[PDB]
Image (tube, rainbow, N blue to C red):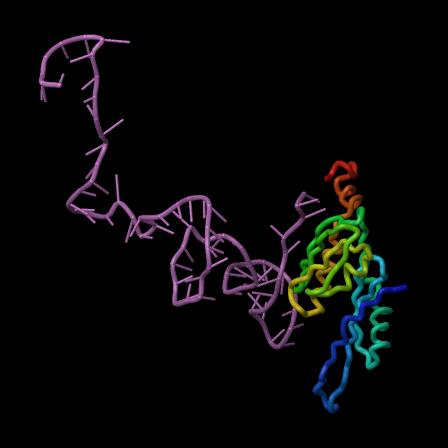
Length: 156
RNA sequence: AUGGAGAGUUUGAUCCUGGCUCAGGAUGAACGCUGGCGGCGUGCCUAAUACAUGCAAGUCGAGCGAAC
């Protein structure tokens, strides 16, 4: 019903009074299995109760990503923090591979025609923030038609 | 619109302007070389570098005086 992508569970070796406190920050993408990105981080002792903790406290950070005719409406970027991304269009009837950054952004948008792009670095805390920067800065067909305030077939 | 766009760099993590140390192809090329065979092309790119040369291109009377 909901494509939840739990990337990893960052641990911490707290060097406080206690011998060695264990704090697992379960990282899970809050995707709605449609086209939204979704990102939430927990801090509970139980990963299962921590993964849903960030899914019930952070589920409004997603963005609606529409599709034209099976191809990305506009090749957007991502200038938020170090890690960056890029939207590359492909044919509707295609697929994705492995080797690079995060995979829970274009995989949520069941279309198999978008290539997930994010160089920046490996840090998965400032690389997903740039993906939502471009997703919210995406240009739609009518979205840009209102900008001019004329016809949809008069701005292409 | 066949539709660019990595980082670091600054506290103990940082955002943010800014500049390049640095994820590539190109390299009229040479290069230390392990450079099987070759179609095709460029070749004193360093050099209007100095000067022994082989060396510019020979002929003709329908119009005139060889021995022929």
